[PDB]
C-alpha cells in the first residue's frame, strides 16, 4: 500500500478452547547480507577437516530462513504448564505465517563514522518452498530460532546445504541449487507476506506416564493356569535329574508368561555426574556407541528412546543417549557439567529398557549331559513381534517436528530426538534482501558487478499454530503429580528476566506428568 | 502506483508441458550514464584504424539495450539437458518482457 | 472360428502417454510334451542329493507355463532408457494376455 | 474367411479418363525364408572390402519387401506410348495396394526327393511402415521389382539396411531396427491385406521438349536498344585505343543481352562409343568426376541434368553422367557396349549446358596497359539468380519416385536419377512368413530354437495408381514428333515375347516428344 500505513498489527495472544489451542506469536527480526550475494562452495578443506568422519561438501547461500520449530517459540512457560498438566496428548493442526512492517536500511561507513538511512524503494524477496524441492535444513535442530521471550530481536540465520562428497571432493551426483531459480515475492515497505499450511495427520504425542509397568500387568491375587519348569535337579548328587513344574503365581512373578515385551534397545555407555566414579581415561569418543555409514562413523546421539537410568540412581546418564541443553550464557566449548542442562528420560521406565543395560539374555549352546547351559548377553535387540515402547519426550527447548526422509521404507518414523515426523512438514520460508549495486562504471564491462550497497532489513513475523488436544479422562482417586514453581524464596523469578535484562529458562520441562494405565 | 508498493514479483520458474515449454527468467540490471548524454560520431580515425579492411564510421548513443538472445539466458543446464535428450526439434512461439521495481 | 482365418494380429508397439506407458509385446512359442503325460514324484533320491540342505520332494507335471516377469520381456533397451532417464518412479497397473494362431 | 473361397479377383486393366489415368496391375509373387530367421550384421569385412570408399556396415533381415516403383511395372508399352504422345505432363495422385490369395507351402527334402505340401494353418505377416521409422530402401533403384510382363512370377527381395561406420566397425550412433518390433497383420489363406495412400502434391513431370532454345528468345527482325562494346582497338599500331559501341542486333547475336541463363553444370569426362577415339589407358575410375563425403570418394552418377552430347555428335557420352540399362539376359560384369542400353539426354540441349563442356568462361585478372586480358574456364557453376534448367527425363525402366532425406535444407529436391521426390513417399510394404519350429526337445532348454520347417508362401499383388494428366494445348501448325514402332519386318516383335518365352524391352523410351515454347 503505502509508506505511512502499517502493514499489520502485533498479535501475540493465545486462546484456549476446549479441544483446541491457538497460539499466536509475534517477533521482530533483522536480516543482514550474507556471503556478499554469493554462493561459496563450503567444504571441510576450507578450514581443517583432517578426519574422514568430519568430511563434508556443500554450498552457502546469501539467503536466510525462519526456524520457529522449537517449542519455546510458540508457548510461554505458563501456556506450557497449562498444557501438560491438563492434557494427555496434543498435535498441531494448522499453521499461519505473516511478514509485515518491513523496513530496509542503507548503511554508509566513512571515516569510521556510520549513518544508517532508510531506503523506501528497496525490496526484500521471500518465498516458501512448498514442493520440498530444496534440502530441508529445519529438522536438524540448529540454532537461529525465534527467541523464547517476545521482547527480543533476533537475527535470521544463513541458509546452506550439504551434498554428496568423497572426502572434500564433489561426487558427480552432487546437486547445486540456485535459490534465485524459484518464484518469489518481492516486498517493499507497505507490502506484507502470508501463507497458510495444514499439518498432515500425525499421531498425538503422548504426554503421560504409566501408572503400572509392563512386567506387572497381572492380578496379584490369582494364579496362572500355565506352568513353567521350576526344578531341573532332583537333588544334590550324581544321576539326580528330573523335570518338575509349578504354577506361575503371585509368589513367583517374573517367571509368569505375558503377552508383550519391552521395546528395542541399543546399549549406551554409562557415565556418572559424580566425577570420581567415572574411569580415568578418555572414553568419550572411543567408548561410545556409533553407527557407521559409508566408511564414516556417526556417533549415535538420541537413539531408540530408552530409560536413562534405573530405579533411584540418578548419578549416571547415558553417554550419547540423552539430550543436553545449555543454560543462559553458556560457553561454546569445554563447558563444565553444572552449566549444561541434562535431560531425564526416566518416565518411560515402564515400557522401555534402560539405555545403559542389556535388553536381556539368550542361550548360547545346547545343553547335554556333558555340556552346561551357557547364556550370553543381548547388547542390542532390533525388534520382535509383540514389542511395545514409547517415543522420546517433548520439551520447551526441543524441536517440534522433523522431515521423514523420502525413501522406500521406514519403520515408525517418529524422530529420534523428538517431535512429530512428517513427510511434508511446514515448508521453509527463505528470505533475502535484493541487491542494490553501487554506481556502475561508464564504459561497459562484461564482468558482473561485485560492488553493492551495504544494506539490511527489519520487520515482524507472526506465527500462529492451531493445536489439537486430548483431554484427561482419568478415573484415578489420589492426586496426580503436576509441574510447579517451588515456593521457596530466591533472588530471581524462574522463567523471568534478570536484573541486566536477560531472559533465562532455569530447567528443561518435560511433557509427561499425568499418568495413564499401561 | 507508489513508492512503497512493489511493481512486480520475481518469477523464474519453467514449466514443461507436452508439446510446449515456457521458460521464465528474472535478473537484476544496472544502467549507467553513457557518453555524458551525447552522440559522438565514432570512427576508426579516433584511435588507430590504419587498415582499410578495419575502416568504420558510426555513432555512439547514450542509450543502452537488453540483449537476451543467447541460449544460456533462458535455459538452465538441466532444462537444456531435459530439452535436447527428449526432443528432436524446437522453435520459439511467443515472447513476453517486463521491467519492474525501478530505482534511480 | 476357422482354419483359414487368423486368430489375431501381431501387435508389438509401445505408446508413451504423459503419466502412463502401455507396452505391448508379441512372441512365438513352442510347447512340447512333458513327462509323457505323467506326474513323476521328483525327489533328491532320484539323483544324488547326499546333503540334507539339498533335500527336496515334489512332483513334475506334463503342464507348462508362461513366465514373462523379467523386465527385458516388456521393455526394449530404448524404452528402458526413455523410462529411467525421465522418471522418478513407476509401477504396473493393468495386464492383458492373449494366445492366438495356435498350430498343432 | 475360408480355405475354399478366393480372397480377390485378378484386375489388370487401365482406364483413361480425360484428365486422369488409373492403371491397375496384378502379379504373382513367391516369398522364401531369408537368413534362417536371423539378423546377421552384414559388413564389408565379411567378404573383401579392402577399399575405404567401399566400407559399409549394416544388418540383413529375414523380412522382404515389395518394390514396384519402376515405370514398366504400372504401364504397358502401349499405355506408355498413349501417355507420352498425347500429354505434356503427369504425376501420381493416389495409390492402392492389395495382397490376396495367399498360399503357404511346406517342403520336406529327404533322400534327395522333395515333396511340397500345403500348410493351411500357417501365417504370413505383413505391415506397411507409415511413419517412415525405418531406413527407406526403395528410392535407391535396386532390383527386385514387379516384372514388366504380367505373366511372370517374381521373387520378393530381401530387406536390409546400412548404418554409420568407421571402416567396418560400428560407430556409437549406429542404429539397430528390429522389424518384429512393429505392429503387423498376420494373414492365413483366406485373409487379404490392403491399404490406400495419397501422394502429396508434386510438380508435374514435364514431358515435352522445347521448340526454341534459351539463347534464341528474340525477335530476329528487330534490333535491341541496348549497346555493347564492339571495338576496343582503334586500329593496328601503337597507342591506338578507343571504345566503340554498337547496337546488338540480328547481325550479331550471342552478344545481345538476355534475361535468363542456362542451368548449373558439373563437368563429366567425355568417352566415345567408337573404340579407337578413346584414349589408351584406364581413365574409368581415375578420370571420373566424384564427390567426397567424410573421406570417401563417391563417384558422381547422374548429377545435374545436362545434355549428354552437343549437336549431331552421338559418338560420345558422359562417363558417369548418363543412365545405362541392360538388355534382356545381359551379363553381370564386363559386359560389352552393345549389350548395355545407353540413354540419350539430348532433349534438354535448349535449357541445359552440355555435360562434357564447361559452363562458360570468366576473366582471371584486371587488364591494364601492361597486362593482357586473361580468361579461365568454368568447370562447375553452382547457381546464379536467373538460371533456368530442366530435370532428367523419365523412362519405362527408370524409377517413379524417391524419398527426400529429412534435413534442414535442400535445393530443388527433384531426384538426380529421375522421378518425383517426396518427403513422404508411398510407404514400404514388408512381408515375412512366420516361423514354424520343428519338434522341440522334451527336456526344457534355455536356448532359442534354431530348427524350423522349410517353408514359403505365394499370392497375388494388385497395385493401382491414379495419375493426373496435363493435356497438350499446342497451337503448332506442322506435325509433332511421336514415338512409333518402325514398320520394317523383323524376326520378332518389339516389346513382345521371344520364341523361348522371354519378354524383352528393345530400347529405352524417354518421356519427351511433344514440344512447348521456351
Image (spheres, coloured by chain):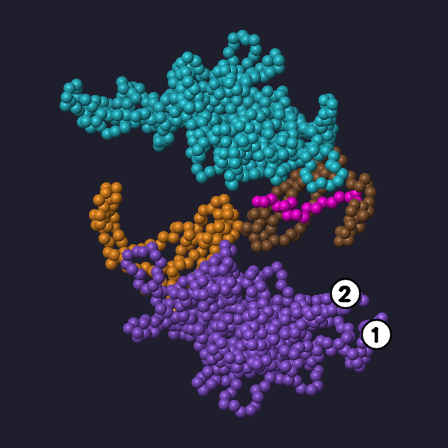
Chain colours: A purple, B orange, C brown, D cyan
The C terminus of chain B - image quarter: bottom left
Residue D81 visible in the current orientation: no
Mark before the other along the chain sequence, 2 or 1: 1
Tell me: residue A324, above or below residue C27: below
Picture quarter containing residue A47?
A: bottom left
Question: Label 2's element?
Answer: loop
Q: Which residues are magenta?
A: C58-78
Q: Which residue is mark 2?
A: A366
Question: Label 1's element?
Answer: loop
Which percent across, then down, holds residue A261?
A: 71, 71
Q: Which residue is mark 1?
A: A237
| Magenta highlight: main SS | loop
Q: Nearer the viewer, residue A39 or C94?
A: A39
Which percent across, then down, holds residue A253?
A: 77, 78
Nearer mark to the viewer, of 2 and 1: 1
Q: Residue at x 32, y 59 (%)?
A: B31
Residue C70 forms part of the magenta stretch: yes
Picture quarter containing residue A202?
A: bottom right
Q: Which mark is residue A121?
A: none
Q: Residue at x 42, y 62 (%)?
A: A40
The N terminus of chain B - image quarter: bottom left
Which percent across, then down, holds residue A465?
A: 55, 74
Disc 2 to disc 1, C-alpha distance: 22 Å
Badge 2: residue crowd in 10 Å (few <14, some 14–19, many ≥20): few
Tell me: residue A315, above or below residue C53: below
Q: Nearer the viewer, residue A286 or B1?
A: A286
Q: Nearer the viewer, residue D246 or B81?
A: B81
Which percent across, then down, holds residue D115?
A: 73, 24
Q: Residue at x 41, y 12 (%)?
A: D276
Q: Residue at x 58, y 74 (%)?
A: A319
Name the chain under label 2.
A
Picture quarter containing residue D11?
A: top right
Amino acid at each position: 500500500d503505502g509508506v505511512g500505513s502499517s502493514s499489520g498489527n502485533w498479535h501475540c495472544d493465545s486462546q484456549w478452547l476446549g479441544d483446541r489451542v491457538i497460539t499466536t506469536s509475534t517477533r521482530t527480526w533483522a536480516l543482514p547480507t550474507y556471503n556478499n550475494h554469493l554462493y561459496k562452495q563450503i567444504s571441510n578443506s576450507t578450514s581443517g577437516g583432517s578426519s574422514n568422519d568430519n568430511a563434508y561438501f556443500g554450498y552457502s547461500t546469501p539467503w536466510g530462513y525462519f526456524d520457529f520449530n522449537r517449542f519455546h517459540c510458540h508457548f510461554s512457560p505458563r501456556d506450557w504448564q497449562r498444557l501438560i498438566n491438563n492434557n494427555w496428548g496434543f498435535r498441531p493442526k494448522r499453521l499461519n505465517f505473516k511478514l509485515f512492517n518491513i523496513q530496509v536500511k542503507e548503511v554508509t561507513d566513512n571515516n569510521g563514522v556510520k549513518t544508517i538511512a532508510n531506503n523506501l524503494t528497496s525490496t526484500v524477496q521471500v518465498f516458501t518452498d512448498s514442493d520440498y524441492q530444496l534440502p530441508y535444513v529445519l529438522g536438524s535442530a540448529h540454532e537461529g530460532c525465534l527467541p523464547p521471550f517476545p521482547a527480543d530481536v533476533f537475527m535470521i540465520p544463513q541458509y546452506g546445504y550439504l551434498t554428496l562428497n568423497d572426502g572434500s571432493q564433489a561426487v558427480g551426483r552432487s546437486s547445486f541449487y540456485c535459490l534465485e531459480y524459484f518464484p518469489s515475492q518481492m516486498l517493499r515497505t507497505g507490502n506484507n507476506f502470508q501463507f497458510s499450511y495444514e499439518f498432515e495427520n500425525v499421531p498425538f504425542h503422548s504426554s503421560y506416564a504409566h501408572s503400572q509397568s509392563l512386567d506387572r500387568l497381572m492380578n496379584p491375587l490369582i494364579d496362572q493356569y500355565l506352568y513353567y519348569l521350576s526344578k531341573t535337579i532332583n537333588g544334590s548328587g550324581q544321576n539326580q535329574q528330573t523335570l518338575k513344574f509349578s504354577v506361575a503365581g503371585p509368589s513367583n512373578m517374573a517367571v509368569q508368561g505375558r503377552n508383550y515385551i519391552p521395546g528395542p534397545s541399543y546399549r549406551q555407555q554409562r557415565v556418572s555426574t559424580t566425577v570420581t566414579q567415572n574411569n580415568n581415561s578418555e572414553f568419550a569418543w572411543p567408548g561410545a556407541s556409533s553407527w557407521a555409514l559409508n566408511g564414516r562413523n556417526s556417533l549415535m546421539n538420541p537413539g531408540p528412546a530408552m530409560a536413562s537410568h534405573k530405579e533411584g540412581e540418578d548419578r549416571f546418564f547415558p553417554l550419547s543417549g540423552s539430550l543436553i541443553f545449555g543454560k543462559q550464557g553458556t560457553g561454546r566449548d569445554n563447558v563444565d557439567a553444572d552449566k549444561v542442562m541434562i535431560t531425564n528420560e526416566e518416565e518411560i521406565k515402564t515400557t522401555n529398557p534402560v539405555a545403559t543395560e542389556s535388553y536381556g539374555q539368550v542361550a548360547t549352546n545346547h545343553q547335554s549331559a556333558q555340556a552346561q547351559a551357557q547364556t550370553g548377553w543381548v547388547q542390542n535387540q532390533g525388534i520382535l513381534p509383540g514389542m511395545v515402547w514409547q517415543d522420546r519426550d517433548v520439551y520447551l527447548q526441543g524441536p517440534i517436528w522433523a522431515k521423514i526422509p523420502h525413501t522406500d521404507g521406514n519403520f515408525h518414523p517418529s524422530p529420534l530426538m523428538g517431535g512429530f515426523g512428517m513427510k511434508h512438514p511446514p515448508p521453509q520460508i527463505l528470505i533475502k534482501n535484493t541487491p542494490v549495486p553501487a554506481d556502475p562504471p561508464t564504459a561497459f564491462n562484461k564482468d558482473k558487478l561485485n560492488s553493492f550497497i551495504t544494506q539490511y532489513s527489519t520487520g515482524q513475523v507472526s506465527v500462529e499454530i492451531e493445536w489439537e488436544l486430548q483431554k484427561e479422562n482419568s478415573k484415578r482417586w489420589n492426586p496426580e503429580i503436576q509441574y510447579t514453581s517451588n515456593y521457596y524464596k530466591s533472588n530471581n523469578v524462574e522463567f523471568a528476566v534478570n536484573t541486566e535484562g536477560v531472559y533465562s529458562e532455569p530447567r528443561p520441562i518435560g511433557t509427561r506428568y499425568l499418568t495413564r494405565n499401561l
